[PDB]
Image (cartoon, coloured by chain):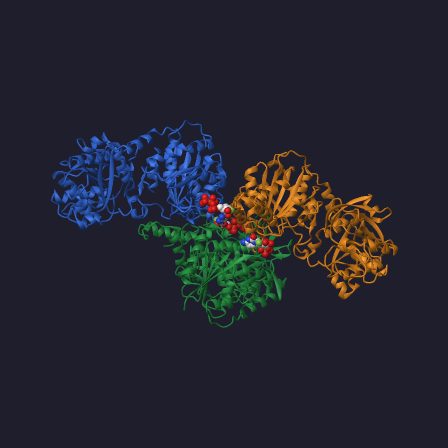
Chain colours: A blue, B green, C orange
Amino acid sequence: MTTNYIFVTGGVVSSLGKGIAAASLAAILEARGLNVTIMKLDPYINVDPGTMSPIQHGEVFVTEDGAETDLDLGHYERFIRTKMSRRNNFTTGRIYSDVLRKERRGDYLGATVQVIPHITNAIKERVLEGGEGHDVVLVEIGGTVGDIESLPFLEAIRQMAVEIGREHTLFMHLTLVPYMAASGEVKTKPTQHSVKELLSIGIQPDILICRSDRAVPANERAKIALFCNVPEKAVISLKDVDSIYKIPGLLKSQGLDDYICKRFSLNCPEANLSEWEQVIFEEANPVSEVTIGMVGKYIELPDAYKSVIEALKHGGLKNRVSVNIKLIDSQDVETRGVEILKGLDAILVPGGFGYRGVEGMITTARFARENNIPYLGICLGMQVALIDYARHVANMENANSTEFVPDCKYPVVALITEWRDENGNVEVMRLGAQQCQLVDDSLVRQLYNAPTIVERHRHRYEVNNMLLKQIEDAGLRVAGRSGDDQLVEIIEVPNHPWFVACQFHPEFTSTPRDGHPLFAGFVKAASEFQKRQ
Amino acid sequence: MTTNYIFVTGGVVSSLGKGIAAASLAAILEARGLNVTIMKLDPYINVDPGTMSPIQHGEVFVTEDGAETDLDLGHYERFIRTKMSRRNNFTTGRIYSDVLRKERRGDYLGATVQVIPHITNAIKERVLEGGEGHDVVLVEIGGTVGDIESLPFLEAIRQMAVEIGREHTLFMHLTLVPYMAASGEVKTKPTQHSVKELLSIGIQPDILICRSDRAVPANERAKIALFCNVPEKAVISLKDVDSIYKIPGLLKSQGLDDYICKRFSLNCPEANLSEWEQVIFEEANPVSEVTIGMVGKYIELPDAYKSVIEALKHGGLKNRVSVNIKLIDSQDVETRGVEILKGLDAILVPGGFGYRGVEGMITTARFARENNIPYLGICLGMQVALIDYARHVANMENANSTEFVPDCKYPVVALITEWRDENGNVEVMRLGAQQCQLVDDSLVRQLYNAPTIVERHRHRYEVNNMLLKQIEDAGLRVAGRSGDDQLVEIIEVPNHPWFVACQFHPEFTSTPRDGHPLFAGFVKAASEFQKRQ
Amino acid sequence: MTTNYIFVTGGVVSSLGKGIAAASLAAILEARGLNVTIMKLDPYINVDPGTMSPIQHGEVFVTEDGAETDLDLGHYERFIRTKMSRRNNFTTGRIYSDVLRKERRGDYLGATVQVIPHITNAIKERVLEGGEGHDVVLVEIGGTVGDIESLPFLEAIRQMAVEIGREHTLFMHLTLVPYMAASGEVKTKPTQHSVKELLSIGIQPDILICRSDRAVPANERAKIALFCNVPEKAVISLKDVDSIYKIPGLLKSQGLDDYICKRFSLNCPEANLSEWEQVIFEEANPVSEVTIGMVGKYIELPDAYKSVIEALKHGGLKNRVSVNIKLIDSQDVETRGVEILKGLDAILVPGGFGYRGVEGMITTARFARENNIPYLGICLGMQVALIDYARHVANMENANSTEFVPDCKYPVVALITEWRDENGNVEVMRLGAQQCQLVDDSLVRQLYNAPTIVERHRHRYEVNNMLLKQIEDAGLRVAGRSGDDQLVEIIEVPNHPWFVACQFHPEFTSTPRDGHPLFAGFVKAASEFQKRQ
Ligand SMILES: Nc1ccn([C@@H]2O[C@H](COP(=O)(O)OP(=O)(O)OP(=O)(O)O)[C@@H](O)[C@H]2F)c(=O)n1
Ligand SMILES: Nc1ccn([C@@H]2O[C@H](COP(=O)(O)OP(=O)(O)OP(=O)(O)O)[C@@H](O)[C@H]2F)c(=O)n1
Ligand SMILES: Nc1ccn([C@@H]2O[C@H](COP(=O)(O)OP(=O)(O)OP(=O)(O)O)[C@@H](O)[C@H]2F)c(=O)n1
């Protein structure tokens, strides 16, 4: 059976929720038994987001295969069960890097290498690579139509539509239909001007997704249908919602998936959105409420912790607990003290690099441990837990990571090559999914309810096994290990209601439907702490 | 004093002669005592033309510093005395390569790298690097305004004009004003639509250069002046000409250089175009005529030998000889025989790579030597001369280059590392200007009238010094050497009216005003041969 | 029965021959037995060309129904037998007049009247009115796509194509593919940019008609086919031709009519162009040559006499005579005398208004009559012939028209209301087709071979019947009359080889295939005169 492509573009503004719209539609199509995947084309020149700052870009999402990707692939995995890889995200940078590699090598046989056809060919090849073997492929084009940065992507998908044909390709264009107080109506003029930009570069939209702060009435949808020459049922209202989990239902209620299946001649049963209806019900009917402090160094952009924030929400769903997430700057802990950590039912220290704000995170880990406040440390969160325990229980003065203090006496965290003890004696970037072995009688062995788990890494600095035994003797427990080097993956403080810290990023395998054993356990502990007060 | 920039763009069609127009204007400004330079921005993705085929792109021009550049830099050096370097030519490929290098390295400090401002910043930086330190910098933008490939270049120069100001920047736009038989007039409508494209990307043209197959009358120039909102004296007619040497005079006669000097507030004397008037006079008043056969493997695109064709014309000027250049396919010599080399007053075998057509060039060199027909071999032309002499005089059976027959018994041409004799015994890409030492009592020592010369290389395969002495004993003379390895640069056949072959590319230092000693000597010999018949 | 529409647009330049191309294609379709018509949409604000000067816009063409139309309707009637009416030509001025009339009287029921939908609706209504009841309707859109003046027309026909559908509508776009000497090739870049402007206003061309001064090769046509996403058979080469009569054959040979009949599902036999082949043959093979002087007051624009020039050519075809048309300014006859009328085989005085140059035409008529030089007078040409005969034979001194000298003693030409005799005693704009009664034994009765004819008028001033009988008695013969007032339509001078003058415009009923009895007779007399000299 022929692979079908839905090209997802945006007009008027960038922040239309193209990713959430594509992911929500993919969820409906998957619920009709279709094999669906999603792909993100980013017009930035960065070869990948591995270099990009969290406070500039948002979180770097990590796929099972260890690709560093746009946080949109987090949306994709949280809406469909089709696993994302390197093939589901590429940048203009990646395209030019690969064309330049081929050109300098001599693969173009002395030809003049051109934006058309060579850059556009490279784009089409990567879309086909990610798409072929699926029933429906949703291809999200980053940027706003009319901008120069996305012109090669738009010319590439235009060519694909000509080659493949209108029987197996659709153009789904998101647009802003803004409300004006003065007119007391939503305005289609920006959609008119955006669609004109699309037409000028040879793309006719099949579907209009009308974004607004309210319902786009039938009268306005009728206007858009006429000026775009599309059926009225191909013009969809997507108002601002309190919950993205409702979007699949909102799109299905307007028959969007029916129109797509008709256009692609797909005979498949009606979408059963029971799993999404259940998530919505859970969210709408909490039994109790908690306040969880997230203490990190990137809080100035919450999207720096996108998957962690969603993982905490999923933890809420599974416990019927409403989670109030309080973003706390770890540097404020360094200046103002532990005063700002008061009135928290639990504390989460997420991932990060560089020494800025790390001492505040160590103080935060100490506060949580000493005051029996539920604690979850992720990557850097595990480091500061180990450092806290090394310093203040195992009596290892000024214990630190070689990342922060390279020549510290007790490098309890360090690169495998840097591993040394306090006497200077020695022995004779991990990305993606890896198996972790859980230790018998550990909290995580119970929570995960399995002897082995698979979680995703994005880190280079490990627990120093040369200084580990001393910290173990001081009472800290190793709950998880991995590989031949038996690298520490999970640590637990036993004399504590709930204290867990892991090297891997569990937030990347959390979904609203399936939740996550660790976050479910964490939020449950937060609820139990709140009740005890 | 502030550096002034003239941005040279083209509309309607690619082949307007933007390079020749920029070069011709530069010649006028240089003749007014101004320090002028020219720069070419190519929108192709090739990092440089080093990979690009001659039959696709045209000749690879080599600057003194050994940069492989667009043939436009040949136009530039043939019109102004300001020496070109790597700084006078760059591609989109070069820009992206440098931005990606910086990005992967981490110079953007975790920022999202964007077409604007990061690609445009990289373009502006390279324009400033090539421009600063000159009175006037002409910046030629490759492509046709309205195409996506040149949009980043156009946004970059738009920003430069805002920053620098209209006191020290001008937009000079070439346009096609085509004649229609039906209307019996030249048509400004394409100029109207092209200027609209310029305005849409934020550029207002200051000067319109109107290209046509005839004069653009004052009435039509008046129409263009009004719709562009420029003075009538800023609208220039540049009709098709029989000689590009006339273009400086044609532009000066319409006061283009006066307008530029007024806009840039440059107080400089009137242009004395006597040197160009003399070139025009020489060209228009030849005394005799010759037919010179150019026997190569890229004749399907004459621009493959652009600088060689111009060098032969310059040889004509200095001798008052009209040169009829007959392009002959060396593969036709292999199939049809030496029949197709009849009625030639001289034979030139130019540069090339790969074995295709080389045996035809060896046969051509043999024909010229045996029939006492003046011969000039350039690079590959020298190889086939050495091979011919090795085989047919020094009795070295099947003598060849390791490039063509790697395991041949007599590798008379080979890489320095491959150098071996006929017994297999051994000893215990050159680009740009290098000094060559000329041998006493050689033809070239007389022609160049100096013991040392500087010429430009583009080759990797050398004369094998291990097999050289045997060929010397057979009567071939070494006329030029270079470096510590004493690599053979020039060879001569003594018992011949004029037989010279060189490793370097003398065509790259030939100009219409100064000519070239070697090409002047070659065309003189062609004339003397013609008279003898 | 469903009516099919071919929308004919032009890009790059105005003077593509959109009318000749539309008319030529119509001729092929008519030769397949199809009922075809053509209409011209003119973007000028003139309600009609009734006001527009001959020396600015060219001849006012008169249809049977007495509409004053664009000279393109002359092309239409010379290529197809379908009669043009007021319905086959309208301007922007007509459309705005239509809408303003409806608005002021209150047909829009207090609605805001808008370019869309009210102006576009008015355009569509007139296109349907002219089109319905035909197999194929060719709709020529005046102007160049990308200009603001034609935007409402282009939006109107865009809407029609959506309503009617691609099964019964086609967009045929003429484009300029200009030759550049520099590249030695025709350039598709203007077509690329023109088609983008078409796409931007929501029109995708089906057929590309490629205009150039030479054949557009298959390689360039293939390039255009790909970038336009049309079949290669939908890209047509239409080079400059020496005869417009060849264009139907040239379009047929590339199968354009086959493609149109396929797209519209029209099963019709092959085009029989035998009549066009005959016209081409006749034109190419003249037996003899004649010089015919056209003495008028609008010669500064030949298009002022478009249909008269074509009628003289058609006279040539039917006699196998090459007609050298010498345009002579009648004012030069006034200043330089009858010297400038020497070396003419025949004299034609065409239509005109106002006194400027009329005395020169009267002198011209006298010269032709006295020297027995074949004479054909049309409208004003009949007036001056009557004035000549009145003055110089009937001895009516200073005889004139009331248009020129209102108070003249002998107003031999005057409005019916002004009719008076020499003593001042009294009795008691004609547009379109009218029956004229031909007098027995007259030359015109013999040539037309019918007692009655139908010819078209555009005049105000009649022959004064009160002064007629005195001119008749002096030898002049009335050859044709019309109406109840027995108005003089044709006069003849008996003692002369060929002297005819008519009130009506016979040039409007002349075609290359059928010729015209008066013009055929006139050119025959010119050849017979040339033989005698
Ligand atoms: N390509 C176009 C399309 C339309 N028009 C003009 O546009 C006017 C209505 O334009 P309005 O902003 O008043 O109302 P609307 O379009 O429904 O847009 P909105 O309220 O939903 O935002 C109307 O006279 C029409 F002539 C145009 O000139 N050129
Ligand atoms: N942005 C523009 C500019 C002009 N126009 C229209 O353009 C018409 C003349 O357009 P023409 O091709 O006949 O003559 P031209 O322009 O002198 O061009 P050319 O012969 O030198 O090629 C004229 O009615 C004017 F209304 C337009 O609609 N939109
Ligand atoms: N929307 C477009 C379309 C094309 N391009 C660029 O256009 C270059 C060839 O452009 P050329 O004038 O050399 O050749 P051509 O197109 O065949 O036109 P012609 O000779 O028939 O007139 C080529 O690198 C391609 F990348 C563009 O940037 N934007």
Question: Residue A223 vs residue A142: left or right?
Answer: right
Q: Is residue B333 visible?
A: yes
Q: How many marks?
A: 0
Q: Position of residue A517 (x, y in %)?
A: 24, 33
Please name whichever residue, A68 or C495, is drawn nearer the observer in this view of the structure. C495
Q: Is residue C200 visible?
A: no
Q: Position of residue B350 (x, y in %)?
A: 52, 56
Quarter that holds the N terminus of chain C: top right
Q: Where is residue C2, by image quadrant?
A: top right
Within the displayed image, which quadrant is ligand 2 positioned in? bottom right
Quarter that holds the C terminus of chain C: bottom right
Please name whichever residue, A61 or B291, is drawn nearer the observer in this view of the structure. A61
Q: Relative to B173, does residue C48 appear above or below in the rendering?
A: above
Q: Position of residue B474 (x, y in %)?
A: 50, 58
Q: Position of residue B226 (x, y in %)?
A: 54, 60
Q: Relative to B281, does residue B147 appear above or below in the rendering?
A: above
